[PDB]
Length: 369
Ligand SMILES: Nc1ncnc2c1ncn2[C@@H]1O[C@H](COP(=O)(O)OP(=O)(O)O)[C@@H](O)[C@H]1O
Ligand SMILES: [Ca+2]
Ligand SMILES: [Ca+2]
Ligand SMILES: [Ca+2]
Ligand SMILES: [Ca+2]
Ligand SMILES: [Ca+2]
Ligand SMILES: [Ca+2]
Image (cartoon, rainbow, N blue to C red; front, top):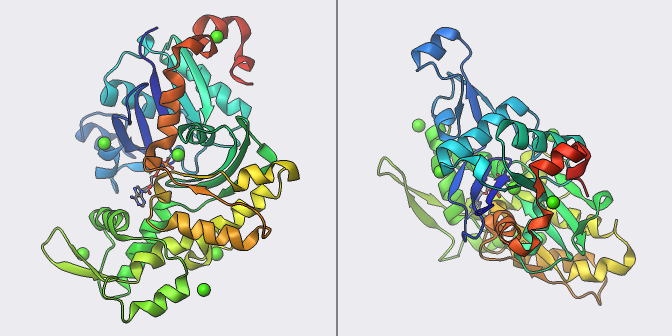
């Protein structure tokens, strides 16, 4: 036992690295691609499968799969390929030398955590492992053990209330909208101005425009009203062919979808309503602690303006005397991984790891509680 590994299994991105590093060394797409024809398989190099950017480059030829599409792992043969890629191709480690901490989505079934554990020990021969809930790790990365996390990533968004380290399962809310939807919606709305962003390459360009220029308006209708005379709304962006496009109200219309899912044709409540609905499914006596500790996590919470908008919307739904605080750490794109890194580097607590001997002696029930 020397250096622990942290693997945050994201719906769109795997974040992995060594405990104790400040950020993950390896970040790649959680996609597996498989040829559909034997001749194509052999002609492209005899590889049975491709993972990450290699898989994405071969789209249209390979069948792509997202084995963690909405945060829960649904295909174990594909997941084994992602973990093999993580260990051998990205981190370049021998997994049998490292205790490995894995993350899991809110509401992950016990049988799913058991299958994750079985693969780590039987397939990769890790010496020890541990599974932690992603939102709890993000709460720890913010330095608290009580609070409600809003975690918006690539394929899913959750609201997870947590009391003294315990996620309250009956109050967890899941919204199947997150960054991949926002990138698709920005491609569509830019195509409204006479531009054309439709190819794989164009989606990557639009993902860059989203991450660099979008923001959350404090009020959508008033921001639209200010747009005509604003001297700072319009931004220019140079494309790869040297053309320059102008982006204006699309900067805030795109992320407005998190608060108004009807923009992409979803009937769901927006993230401020799900936050409130989650707090109201908790014991009345812990709500004050949740309202004062709303922690944002995940890549899709990176927009400038999001904390102020969430403060405004939550204030409008909560009792008038309620103290409301939104915490949006600067490193929140990686706060799940960072929480895992903090936890896995606490060698004083090395007995919390599940070792291979313990698993062999106790069975699959050992990874829970
Ligand atoms: N600065 C940013 N602004 C807006 N979205 C961002 C930013 N940085 C990353 N994202 C988006 O966040 C998503 C990835 O977030 P992440 O928390 O890693 O997701 P997951 O864990 O579900 O894979 C992608 O959709 C990405 O485009
Ligand atoms: Ca995630
Ligand atoms: Ca990468
Ligand atoms: Ca084109
Ligand atoms: Ca309004
Ligand atoms: Ca619909
Ligand atoms: Ca132990």
